[PDB]
Amino acid sequence: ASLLDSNFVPINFTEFVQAISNTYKQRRIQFYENLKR
Amino acid sequence: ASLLDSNFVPINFTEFVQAISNTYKQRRIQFYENLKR
Amino acid sequence: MKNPQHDASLLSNSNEFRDKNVEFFASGGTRTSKFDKLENHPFLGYPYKRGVKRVIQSHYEPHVEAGGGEDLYGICIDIDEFSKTATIVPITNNFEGYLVAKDSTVKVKDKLIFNKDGALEKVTINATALTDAKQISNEVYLVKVAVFGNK
Amino acid sequence: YSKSMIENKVFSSCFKSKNERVDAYSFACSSYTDKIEEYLYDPANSFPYKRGVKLVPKENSIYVEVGADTDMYGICVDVCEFSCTAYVLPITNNFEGYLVTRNPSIKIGEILDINNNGVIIKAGGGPPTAINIYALSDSFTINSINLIKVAIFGNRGLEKT
Amino acid sequence: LFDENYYAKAVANIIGEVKDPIMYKWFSPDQIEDVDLQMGYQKTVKWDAFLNANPTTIANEVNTISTIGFSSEVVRLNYLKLQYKFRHLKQTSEKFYTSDSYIGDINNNLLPFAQAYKLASSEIIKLINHFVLTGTVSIQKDGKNQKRLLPNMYGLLNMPEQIKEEVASGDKDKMDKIFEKIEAGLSKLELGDEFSTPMMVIVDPATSLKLVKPYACEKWEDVLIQTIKAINNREDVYIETSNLLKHKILIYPLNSELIKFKPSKYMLPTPNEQVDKDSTDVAHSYIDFVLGGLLATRKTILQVNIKQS
Amino acid sequence: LFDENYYAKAVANIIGEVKDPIMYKWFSPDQIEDVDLQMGYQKTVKWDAFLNANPTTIANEVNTISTIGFSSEVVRLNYLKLQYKFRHLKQTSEKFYTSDSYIGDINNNLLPFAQAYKLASSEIIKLINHFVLTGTVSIQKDGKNQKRLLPNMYGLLNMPEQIKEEVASGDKDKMDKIFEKIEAGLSKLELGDEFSTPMMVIVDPATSLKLVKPYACEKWEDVLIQTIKAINNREDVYIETSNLLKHKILIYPLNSELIKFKPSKYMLPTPNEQVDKDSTDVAHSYIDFVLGGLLATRKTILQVNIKQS
């Protein structure tokens, strides 16, 4: 359940918050993947 | 015979120890392959 | 040595089943229990079938050497020459077997003490002789004893 | 005192010399066929952990209390504080492990004796020793409690000086 | 839910426009691990093993074998929940304020919910980054009027039981003295068996300006990098500049075995279900965030403060 | 087997979480070759060829032709088997100790078999790495109470018939004297026709700190690298820092024709089939490992020791 997935449709606010947290985690993972030093 | 394979089903403790040794050797080979000094 | 490895040219006739256990190569004890404590220790010299004392000092771990008296620590029942190790039954564990005696004066019903060389000599007491001293070879005497501790 | 002894704000900082802990495993070298017994101990008189203990038959149960070498039953190797139960290795069995001492300066190979508090001290104090105790390592202080590695093997035939 | 919650729909639509926090550059990917909590305390248990004696040689028959002992350590971490409130235009009132290529009251500083939430989330992310870097919560450049926080809640700068060095006010402009203090702190650093790890240094603009000066054709930055490489097994040394610091130098390894960040998975801004509505066109919304979760081992962070007076 | 041996199943499941030994970084991939032996001795025979005279020109008729001779050399290597014992909880009892987010008795320092085995294996791997680097077995920081080892069981630091250099205690802080000793050792080094090979140098943290000092805009490390490149046909030169060394410098090539590690394929920790069980919830398990197997040609290792007293 991630907001980045267009197919995802939340049912309630709890699922919305879980999707927000998953999206933040995925964004952090993507940032660490794309980071160069 | 190595512990990495999901299809590998050891029969006895001797086979288990042989699989452990093979897994250690494969891990050493993988480490040397991935090592970049 | 415990097992002197020498090549022979002819086979030795060995069919009699009596008087075949009293030998220097027979390690362990005549009667042994599964619940006997055995400790492997580095050794110096050749304390095989003798009382062993723990000697503590590049610094190295303490070892064991032939001895007895107030410094007595255990009895050496088996030896591994390749690893230079000795299996020891501690003095707190009773032992029954053939051990090295100082001379042939030891007889049955004799109380025996481990001397400074780890050999059993007549009279604290350490062992009770079960058989007479038997000369395996030269001056080597083996006597069956039942070790019980120190008096 | 206790063995476990607490929330920390930060974690505590090679493999060498990591065994110097008060709650470390007492047996330096263990062995199956070692006899271990359970007894009760006084929860307000003396903490018997890593000390020489004696059997005191009370009117309700047999307790173990810290004792001297003259009347020593064994060595207390572990304690369960939840049940206030002490685990004892009888003196008839060998021991090689870390015990509580009161002298912060003891060398290796020295002869040792257990005092009335179940504490390792130098055998030159004067009391005639009745147990074979030898120091396998120098005494070390944990900051404060002093510990030392010792080997205990049975009683001594004639009491020494 | 989206058919009924316009605010939730807008949050889901505009959640991607918020920039990533800059604190991620201060940690390795393996150092960060989320936890499930909002407010309270959590206990972390670390297990270790040690050898009790020399290994036992297996020859013939033997029953006494050397032993391997175990130990545990417990560390408590505190997590705090904080909230902010912001005003915005009601959904049904947007059509009456959609101007030429822009929506909102310029005179009254009223904004659509999506833009207001995006800006508030950016500000809260900046505040969270400041708290993570410093360990204090403040909205003033002086760093005063700090919000009182619970114990066991520290940043990289105020972590206890670390190597603290102080440069006297008389040597505030002496790079030689500053580097001497840095060398002393590096020597006092304790990495143990995890020394082969990249290192991270965080400095302030004044410190960077002093560093880029020539070494008294080499630079103080190069000398510091070589010194840190002498201890980190010739591995990577990263240098960063942050305006949140003031005459402070932070040195720490990027190893998960020494320093671990375990933030709540609700740490980043999250909208609240409650929305304040009335008969007017102005509504109010709430944003929640969680602070806390930095953990470090003793004597692994070097904090150098250059006193100005 | 897995249907009956829960301990074997757990070992198979968690065997992948043990990190690789650090000793692999000190050898080339071709330098290591496993052998099949637990405890005992193995004799390795090396064959060589030589020319007896100048080659014979083939012209017209001739029957007397120059000959090529052969020679052999036998080297004996000793391998020792060692064991450790560790206590752990019982499988049927883990359910009564499965707490929130962790398993095991914090008060009693009791762990599940998998975690206990992982920690014990990590400790044993550290001990094996120390033995390989140094050649001695000890668990004390002072390096005393060493376990006496069999002959023909040498490490890199105690291998006989190699170049040994000693830096006097009065010159312990003189990098020029240390480098002069290093140059003398390098001159005494004999590689023959196998000189074109990469070189490895291992230094203590103190020597690493001294190396980054300016040469007396060049560094002592750079000068040493250039000197080693002068002798190794300008191949790669690798520098490593180890906390297991104290005032010691090790220099040796990474050529399999000069130095070869032939460890037992059971050298790394391996569980034992015997498990001690009783009526209580505590069980004991055994781990086996094998030590020995380093072979080196004469006068191919430079060992510099800086005396402190």
Image (tube, coloured by chain):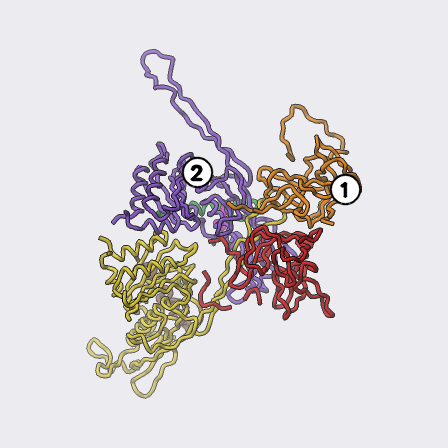
Chain colours: A brown, B green, C orange, D red, E yellow, F purple
| Label 1 Cα neighbours within 10 Å, binned few <14 / some 14-19 / many ≥20 | many
**Which residue ends up furthest to the right in the rendered image?**
C109
Quick check: can you spot residue B11?
A: no
Q: Secondary structure at mark 2?
A: strand
Query: Disc 2 marks which residue?
Result: F260
| Location of residue D46 (image quadrant) | bottom right
Q: Which residues are magenta?
A: B2-6
Q: Position of residue E59 (x, y in %)?
A: 60, 42
Tell me the chain of label 2.
Answer: F
Provide the secondary structure element on which disc 1 rests: strand
Q: Residue at x 33, y 75 (%)?
A: E138
Is E126 magenta? The answer is: no
Q: Residues within 10 Å of mark 2 (few under 14, many from 20)?
A: many
Badge 1 amino acid? Ala
Q: Residue at x 22, y 59 (%)?
A: E213
Name the spot of residue F298 as percent of width and height, x first: 42, 34
| Magenta stretch: helix, strand or loop mostly | loop
Q: Nearer the viewer, residue E64 or F160?
A: F160
Q: What chain letter is assigned to the residue under label 1?
A: C
Q: Is residue F91 left or right of residue B4?
A: right
Looking at the rendered image, the disc whose residue lies closer to the viewer, 2 or 1, is 1
Q: In which quadrant of the rendered view does residue D43 lie?
A: bottom right
Q: CA distance from mark 2 to mark 1?
A: 56 Å
Closer to us: E206 or E155? E206
Q: Which residue is mark 1?
A: C129
